[PDB]
Amino acid sequence: GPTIYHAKDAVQATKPDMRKPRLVVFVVGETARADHVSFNGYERDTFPQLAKIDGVTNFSNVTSCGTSTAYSVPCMFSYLGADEYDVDTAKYQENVLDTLDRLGVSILWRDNNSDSKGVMDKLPKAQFADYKSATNNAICNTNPYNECRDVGMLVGLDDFVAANNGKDMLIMLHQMGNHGPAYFKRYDEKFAKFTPVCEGNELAKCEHQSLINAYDNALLATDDFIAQSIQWLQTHSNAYDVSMLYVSDHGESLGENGVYLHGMPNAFAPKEQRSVPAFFWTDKQTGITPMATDTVLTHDAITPTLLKLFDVTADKVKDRTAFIR
Ligand SMILES: [Zn+2]
């Protein structure tokens, strides 16, 4: 089909041959609720590793585009904004990855969730890698489900950096994260802090506290994955300006008014399905300044954030609020 462009005017103001190349990891999260984040007031410390890392910003007021992976993920990378976004014709629209690629940024998408929901479809197939099986993911045999773990996506990223030495790079890591209903399968035993847990798919038959426990354990694993992503970036901070962005695709209902899981239409969806966490980290030397933690933000902020991270300006999102200055 056709491509309708939105950033043909886009210009990268400076190039990696004149200033430090930039290296960004964007963790595309899954099913995480803002109100179960310690930083947002949650009673449990669900992000203990992130709490110890300097330079992390937590955003307390972020609303997802929609309530499902298929709806939210393409919107996260869209130029159109939630008001004009259409899930069925996103495939015909230039998205922010298309732009950054055109401007010379090396794009990599590793996926331990499903796939990019069409976002990577215009780009060469080799730039997308499936990390849901043991063919690519070296960390799948740590649990009785043989489920591949998000941290497996970090393995061998030095190879990608070496292959693209001196270039700007954007790496998407699409998490399995807190995907349900089987929250108990989403984390290895070392993250089983809150017990007992719900261990079946009939969620309404579990004790509510056990359901919450499994969900919170899954967040601990995500805290770990993000912390290790930051550590990996840190090892490249001499040669690259390094940053990490995390946003979840949507939240999750956990029994409130008897509603479970997600995917409800936006018109009727409860707040829990759209209130998501977002984190930003950057190294001391990058000169990137986060917006105020309580800025009213949505998934619409992702595209101008990614453009700003690579010194690109596009008229379409000129004045649009981002996660960063
Ligand atoms: Zn999802």
Image (cartoon, grey):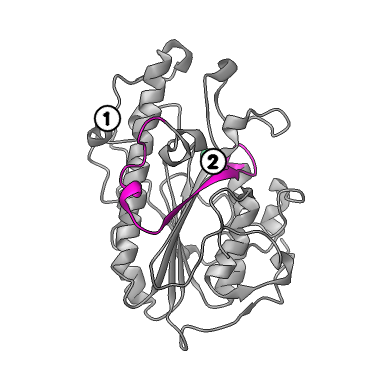
Asked if 49 appears above or below 315 in the picture, the reply is above
The residue lying toward the viewer, choosing from 13 and 155, is 13
Which mark, by number, is residue 276?
2
For image coordinates 73% across by 31% down, the residue present is 267
Tag 1's secondary structure? loop
Tag 2's secondary structure? strand
In this rendering, the count of numbered labels is 2
- Look at the image and tell me in which quarter the N terminus lies: bottom right
Which numbered disc flags the more N-terminal residue, 1 or 2? 1
| Horizontal side of residue 51 vs 111, given as left or right | left
For image coordinates 43% across by 16% down, the residue present is 208
Which mark, by number, is residue 193?
1
Instruction: Name which residue type carries label 2.
Output: Val
Which mark, by number, is residue 315?
none
Using a 10 Å C-alpha cutoff, classify the residue at mark 1 as few (fewer than 14 neighbours), some (14 to 19) or many (20 or more).
some
- The picture places residue 203, in percent across and down from the top left corner, at 45, 17
Would you say residue 50 sits in the magenta stretch?
Answer: yes
| Horizontal side of residue 56 vs 115, given as left or right | left
Would you say residue 233 sits in the magenta stretch?
Answer: no
The residue lying toward the viewer, choosing from 322 and 300, is 322
Question: For the magenta stretch, what is the residue range?
Answer: 43-70
